[PDB]
Image (cartoon, rainbow, N blue to C red):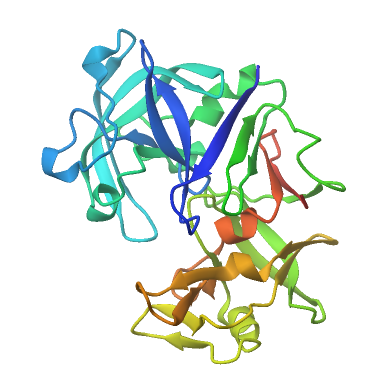
Amino acid sequence: STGSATTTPIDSLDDAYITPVQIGTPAQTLNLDFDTGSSDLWVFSSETTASEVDGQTIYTPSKSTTAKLLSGATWSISYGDGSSSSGDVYTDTVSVGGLTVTGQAVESAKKVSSSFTEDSTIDGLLGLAFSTLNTVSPTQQKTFFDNAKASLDSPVFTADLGYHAPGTYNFGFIDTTAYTGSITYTAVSTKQGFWEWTSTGYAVGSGTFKSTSIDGIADTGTTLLYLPATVVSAYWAQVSGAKSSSSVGGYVFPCSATLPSFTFGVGSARIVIPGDYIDFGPISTGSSSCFGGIQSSAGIGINIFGDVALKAAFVVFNGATTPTLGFASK
């Protein structure tokens, strides 16, 4: 089997991407944030504290003939941006882009933090990291991908995120029309539960390529590209007037600037992020200070190849017995 679903930016900055997901019988369609950096499928629901719902579409298990309470199971998750959610668990039928999993753990939120409430466009998350990170207790649950895997034509999914435009998540096949040139595959470590890999280096604009190992995660659920302070400083040094601002919370630059591209290595291959992808616009409405899309990972504890990087590529998440990641230009 295969599935194919369109993923759509939630706003004009590509802050995140939503993908329609069918849950239950009859189908309830919720728009979920597919997150290769976490492993819980959780939704706003009829159980979510009323004051913490503001415009989201909710899952109502009582209206699904295939929903069953997973008795005694609870979940609680905290994300790198400090947001969080928690609740209980149902199993139900879940379909993405025509691919159906029966018995999927659907984690129903009783509580969500402010950032989720305030984002009316995101109805929940669908995690696509390794199931070892799933937070359900006392019985850990599998991701949608893990559950689908044995039925898939090939044990893969692909992320093809758009720049200010829709893209695609495919399950079970590689669309050879969706990229240019060849796909370069690179080793993954699952030791931390992430799609963790090692980039071979970077370049800033038209500058020479610096060969250097950068361990990080491929994370569709993080907006920006978070890299070591050395690398980030080298990038922003090429933008007149750019500076790191403690008050704003990262690198800012004059909105009048033209940003250089940033290249990262995948083995001997090179993925080029155009400068425009690195512009996240005024720090506040009407400001002439703009927020940068490449930021330091110092104090995160991990480097993160978030959407800024991933959207410059066609990315294969290969979930074979020995997992790997593939990157192609597009």
Residue 173 can be seen in this image: yes
Is residue 306 at least partly visible in the picture? no
Of residues 3 and 72, the one nearer the viewer is 3
178 or 39, which lies in front?
A: 178
| Location of residue 167 by image quarter | top right
Does residue 197 lie above or below 178 as drawn? below
Residue 87 is situated, as x and y percent measured from the top left of the image, at 23, 36
Taking the view exactly as shown, the residue that stands out farthest to the top is: 65
Q: 299 or 72: which is nearer to us? A: 299
Lateral position of residue 182 relative to residue 148, left or right: right
Q: Residue furthest bottom?
A: 241
Q: Is residue 41 left or right of residue 258?
A: left
Relative to 193, does residue 282 appear above or below in the rendering? below
Residue 26 point in image, percent of width and height: 36, 10
Which image quadrant: the N terminus? top right
Q: Position of residue 229 (x, y in %)?
A: 56, 81
- Residue at 67% x, 26% y: name it: 172
Q: Nearer the viewer, residue 10 or 58?
A: 10
Residue in the picture at 42% in, 37% down: 32
Residue 274 percent location from the top left of the image: 69, 66
Residue drawn at x 48%, y 56% is 222
Task: Count every numbered label the image shows and give the total.
Answer: 0
Q: Is residue 306 above or below residue 107?
A: below
